[PDB]
Image (cartoon, coloured by chain):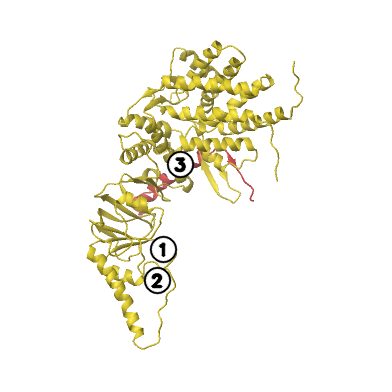
Chain colours: A yellow, B red
Amino acid sequence: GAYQDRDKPAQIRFSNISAAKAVADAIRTSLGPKGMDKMIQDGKGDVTITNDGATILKQMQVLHPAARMLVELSKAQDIEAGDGTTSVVIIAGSLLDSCTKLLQKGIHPTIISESFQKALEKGIEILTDMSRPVELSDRETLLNSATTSLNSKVVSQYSSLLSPMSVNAVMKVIDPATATSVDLRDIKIVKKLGGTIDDCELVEGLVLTQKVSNSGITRVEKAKIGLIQFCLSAPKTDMDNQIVVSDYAQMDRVLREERAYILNLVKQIKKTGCNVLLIQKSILRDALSDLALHFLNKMKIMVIKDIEREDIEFICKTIGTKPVAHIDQFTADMLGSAELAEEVNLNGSGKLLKITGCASPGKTVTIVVRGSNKLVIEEAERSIHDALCVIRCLVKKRALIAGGGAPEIELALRLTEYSRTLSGMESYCVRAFADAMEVIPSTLAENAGLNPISTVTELRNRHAQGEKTAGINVRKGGISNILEELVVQPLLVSVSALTLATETVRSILKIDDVVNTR
Amino acid sequence: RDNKQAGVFEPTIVKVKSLKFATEAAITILRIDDLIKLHPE
């Protein structure tokens, strides 16, 4: 038979596998209802806590290339799902573990991938079979989906309060009809240090982190809002300009007239009847004048400078009020109106602007985060953000699956026989391929501290007639109907996870060498 | 004694927010299971 001369590739392969397995096993601890968040201190000196693996990995300063792709892999999963970033990598590494298994089993890697290509085709087929179609309007199942995602991170503390906040927010921003893929950036997150995670808030309106510029105007009722872009200061041209002084009456005439210019400026604004002012950054040139504020405050008008050009669409998306860049255009026709708006006072003096109630309901919405630990607030929103993501993922496909590993054991079981069906060495690959999925339930019982092998096999043994509804329970610490435990995840989640892993490891196999570069 | 009789009194919210705030932190710190350090660049 043919003789293999070189082993540099094979060993190089093994190196990657050992790395990957080490990586996944390191992450293995954090997953599921018994997931355990981790912490990193930056070399720059920053400190982070995290339960989501992706953020762990984006924190990971990995030296070895392979997992860097795995790190990259999750980001797509994060850019896809949000959790299972947890789950997906442990799937990825587990594949390579068995992929290692086949390596000293001498099978050429190429056939493995196609076998895996076949292996995935069965699974994606199977997963379609087992999923549960669900229309979007059923709030509770969304809620059921929600906490299922949520009881994976610390935010489980106020999960019961947090989950409704999430879903309601989605309902308010979505169209429950087109079943499209509505963006999340239309949802605003507010990291406000202090408070209680319980005191994290939803705002059906607008909130700006910035602070007022008026000393005296604090709360406004029936506010008529105005957002203005053109600066309110000494008129300065884009091109070079200068007033020349050579005569007597130039002084006051200049002096008086700037205020007059400013005066009419404000005069028109008041003439419009607006009462709350929004001012963007004009860092290229002059901003709002101090003098105008004197007038506007004399005109008793709410005012805010320094509005980010990036937020402006969101805000007019939020407030439904087109901005103004020229006086003539500034007209009450465009003047937005709000039922009430003002600056709240928290943090003792961490004061924040609130705008509740809008005659034009924008689809967008903002979200308030309160809580003691600064890091915990950031991790909370991560959990909140992914909570949104999975819902949007669920918005993508109106089909539902129980969480808690039951799909996986079904799959491997289903793979177990189909592997038996298929002849050739491919069967072993699929035999191994299914054995890869075996890890996740084992991980659960690990993080459940329960006898994994006894449980998961019994989980298989039950599941031989204990189909996807049933599985290992966390709360009771046994194996039960997970559907009856209301622990359910959208189909695509594992789909994306399963799919994404499959392509990558195929790419993993094709590797033969790494060459150090300049 | 009776600090009620002694007048030794404290504002409620002091303990109130306290027990909350400690709860959160204890919630935070307990969940950790692993630290990873980075030497500076």
Local crowd size for mark 1, using a 10 Å CA cut-off: few (<14), some (14–19), many (≥20):
some
| Front residue of this view, candidates A10 and A403 | A10
Local crowd size for mark 2, using a 10 Å CA cut-off: few (<14), some (14–19), many (≥20):
few
Local crowd size for mark 3, using a 10 Å CA cut-off: few (<14), some (14–19), many (≥20):
some
Seen in the picture, residue A472 relative to A288 is either above or below; the reply is above
Question: How far is disc 1 from disc 2 in space, using C-alphas?
Answer: 12 Å
In the rendered image, residue A270, in percent from the top left (x then y), is placed at 24, 66
Residue pushed farthest bottom? A248
| Front residue of this view, candidates A78 and B22 | A78
Return the chain for callout 2.
A
Question: How far is disc 3 from disc 1 in space, using C-alphas?
Answer: 32 Å
Disc 1 is placed on an element classified as loop
Q: Amino acid at mark 1?
A: Ser
Of marks 3 and 1, which one's residue comes earlier in the chain?
A: 1
Return the chain for callout 1.
A
Residue pushed farthest front? A239
Q: Which residue is mark 1?
A: A282
Q: Residue at x 45, y 22 (%)?
A: A127
User: Does the image show residue A47?
Assistant: yes
Q: Which residue is mark 2?
A: A236
Which of the two marks, 3 or 1, is nearer to us in this view?
A: 1
Label disc, if present, on residue A298 of the rendered structure: none
Check if mark 1's residue and mark 2's residue have beta carbons within 8 Å. no
In the rendered image, residue A151, in percent from the top left (x then y), is placed at 43, 33
Disc 3 is placed on an element classified as helix
